[PDB]
């Protein structure tokens, strides 16, 4: 039919997938802390381990859609499995194993969905793939905005008319029917828009490999659930992957090439840093929003409205959509990014010195997330081939996986013990982390500009 139509369908199903996913992420930590009894340390480590899994998962999932099942087939399978996972989240049973298994299913589903939906856009546009991917990114952002604003409100509302459960599980249901809606979209536009795409979807499904894939999917679901349960297991796995990438980069260097390689290394550790800084919003910043922020949002000086802590995360995509058209009107952009993130974290750090009544800020979250999200926008060029100045393109992925977990253990530095609820005492330990992160980010700014001549040497 058209290229715009195909890109439309893939951006649509993408939009709804991300709607579901972020609809869950916005509430997951608060679920583990408030509804479940987890302490914020375990919440951080677990959610970040899961995040690492989710972000390293599409590696395998991408190869499956290209080389075994149909890219469209794999995408769909991922969507269905995702729906199943959220469905598992929706049943009101406070059984840690149950939720962990649900998370495993979500991980697998994502690994199968994300990289193949991304391949489609690339095949629908065969340099205008950037024109596509930007719009794509925007669709992702509006979806994620809608969900991150909707689901916490569902959580609160249902928790009022009914007792504790569902409330949370209701929200997870919202995610689920989000996925179902997306799948309905695809179904109503399948051969219509998509039509042509995939490396091996031109034939019927090979039931042997489909079987072995579903089996191994169950197996990976189990592996996931177990990794999530035991903190030490997660620690060992992640640490192992760390030794792996350490070794890979160790061997890569073993005269003229080093100008590209060392630069790539400094770059990849910078990426690690940046992803820690990102991971902070999912955890410690979210927790901070929950325990040390006046949920009463005032437009100086009236009242509308009243935040629900999770909804503060919705500030991230909103600001992205707002400041994107402004920026529309060179590894130094990395440095700019790090600096902007820095002053964001200083705003969170300076949240104590001003606007404080115990738990008070509100606007600190807004300007903070503004700066931080701008900083996110500034580093769109994380591309694996971008550091490819010389394996490293691969190891980069795994390192970028571990980065998340590390972000978790960083957010653990502002772990508030459960028996401490006097916010007047909790506020500093957050602003101590946040003021400390601000300084760290500035060092990263120095790193970026210092390694900039090494980018000039190769050229
Ligand atoms: C596709 C992109 C679309 C983006 C727009 C998305 C719209 C978001 C819809 C849901 C918004 C709900 O988010 C907001 O949650 C807060 C906190 O519970 C609600 O707060 C509401 O109930 C609380 C508690 O009874 C009251 O104190 C408050 O006066 C009232 O507004 C708001 O009514 C709601 O606006
Ligand atoms: Zn300071």
Image (cartoon, rainbow, N blue to C red):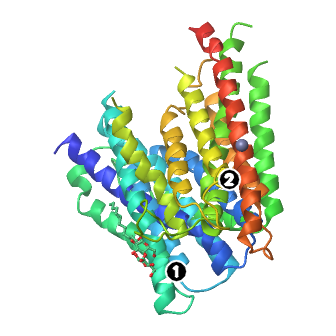
Residue 430 position by quadrant: bottom right
Q: Quadrant of ligand 2?
A: top right
Whether residue 199 is visible, yes or no, is no
The percent coordinates of residue 306 (x first, y second) are 46, 71
Residue depicted at x 57% and y 88%: 164
Instruction: Look at discs 1 and 2 and give the one toward the viewer.
Output: 2
Q: Position of residue 96 (x, y in %)?
A: 69, 78
Residue 75 percent coordinates (x, y): 42, 55
Q: Is residue 31 above or below residue 251?
A: below
Look at the numbered disc 1 and give the secondary structure of its residue: helix
Which residue is labeled 1 in the image? 169
Q: Position of residue 370 (x, y in %)?
A: 49, 47
| Near-viewer residue (331 or 193) | 331
Mark 2 = which residue?
A: 353
Image quarter of residue 49: bottom right
Task: Work out which residue is located at the far left of the displayed protein and give it.
Answer: 1
């Amino acid at each position: 039919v058209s290229k715009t139509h195909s890109f439309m369908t893939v951006s649509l199903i993408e939009l709804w997938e991300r709607f579901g996913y972020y609809g869950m992420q916005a509430l997951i930590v608060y679920f583990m802390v408030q509804r479940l009894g987890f302490d914020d340390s375990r919440a951080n480590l677990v959610w970040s381990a899961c995040a690492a899994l989710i972000y390293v998962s599409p590696a395998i999932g991408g190869w499956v859609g290209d080389k075994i099942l149909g890219t469209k087939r794999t995408m769909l399978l991922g969507a269905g499995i995702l729906s199943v996972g959220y469905a598992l989240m929706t049943v009101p049973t406070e059984n840690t194993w149950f939720m962990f298994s649900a998370l495993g299913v979500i991980v697998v589903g994502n690994g199968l969905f994300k990289p193949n939906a991304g391949n489609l856009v690339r095949k629908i546009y065969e340099s205008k793939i950037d024109s596509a991917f930007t719009i794509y990114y925007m669709a992702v952002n509006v979806g994620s905005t809608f969900s991150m604003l909707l689901t916490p409100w569902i959580k609160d509302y249902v928790n009022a008319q009914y007792g504790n459960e569902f409330g949370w599980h209701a929200a997870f249901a919202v995610c689920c029917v989000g996925i179902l809606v997306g799948l309905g979209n695809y179904a109503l536009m399948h051969k219509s828009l998509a039509n042509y795409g995939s490396e091996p979807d031109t034939r019927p499904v090979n039931k042997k490999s489909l079987a072995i894939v579903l089996a191994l999917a169950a197996l990976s679901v189990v592996a996931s659930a177990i990794i999530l349960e035991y903190e030490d297991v997660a620690r060992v796995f992640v640490y192992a992957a760390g030794v792996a990438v350490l070794g890979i980069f160790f061997h890569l260097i073993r005269p003229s090439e080093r100008a590209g390689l060392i630069a790539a290394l400094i770059l990849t550790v910078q990426t690690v840093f940046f992803f820690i800084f990102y991971q902070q919003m999912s955890t410690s910043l979210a927790l901070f929003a929950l325990r040390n922020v006046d949920w009463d949002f005032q437009v100086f000086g009236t009242h509308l409205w009243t935040w629900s802590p999770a909804q503060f995360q919705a500030l991230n995509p909103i600001w992205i959509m707002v400041l994107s058209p402004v920026l529309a009107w060179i590894a130094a952009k990395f440095a700019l990014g790090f600096a902007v993130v820095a002053i964001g974290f200083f705003i969170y750090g300076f949240a104590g010195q001003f606007a404080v009544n115990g738990k008070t800020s509100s606007w600190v979250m807004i300007w903070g997330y503004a700066s931080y999200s701008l900083g996110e926008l500034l580093v769109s060029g994380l591309g694996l081939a971008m550091i490819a100045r010389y394996f490293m393109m691969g190891a980069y992925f795994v390192a970028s996986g571990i980065s998340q977990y590390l972000g978790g253990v960083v957010a653990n530095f502002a772990s508030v013990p459960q028996d401490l609820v006097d916010p007047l005492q909790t506020l500093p330990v957050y602003t101590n982390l946040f003021n400390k992160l601000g300084v760290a980010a500035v060092v990263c700014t120095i790193i970026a500009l210092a390694v900039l001549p090494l980018m000039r040497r190769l050229t």
